[PDB]
Image 1 (cartoon, rainbow, N blue to C red):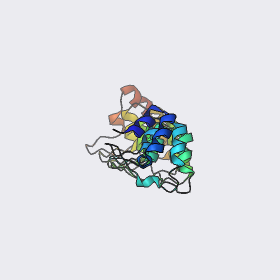
Image 2: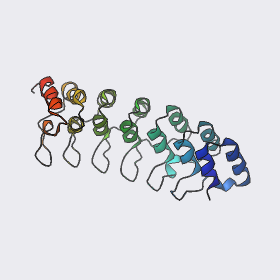
Image 3: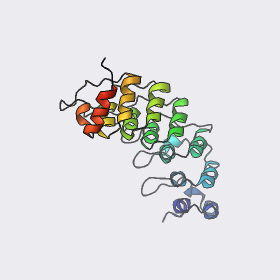
Image 4: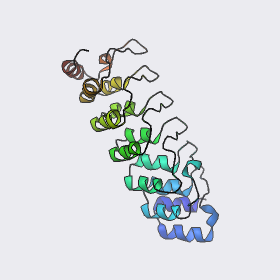
Length: 229
């Protein structure tokens, strides 16, 4: 059915070469998922196969090849977290639009952050990716960083990224709510003390951030370590 895509998934470089020789028009053929062979080689981190495919896609803009979900091969690369592959897709004459969103409104940075891929996230920010693009849920990357409780990512986003801190998603939750709800006390304190997050904001249900804390232990830690403003 889809010989080339499969060979890419299996990481069978010999077969990929064979197939492209007998059926060249398969290079940009879409899946039942709307994916071309490159999506799969990147998805499964087939480094050598990816470079081979790219050598034959010199004039192809990756932005032009979204999944049936809105994911281009660059979105997949950032989600997988292999910085080598990410750099490989970026350092081309035709570069991808770093702020391009999927069908759900998320960016490559949203994807990398939620998976806690620090190196990739940094690479994206250093190259111009905006940290203030909201998805369908009105969340920016910082909402995800607080959710997974990554102190490094929070520092990266708020420091180098100059990320906004008090933006509320559709539930009325700022990143601080997410840190506490998930039990990330140190992350909650960091946002408030170092980056000025406000903790007196209320939910779409009138709840304060301290009110959605995972434990009474987490709540106590938070209240005990934040200064009144």
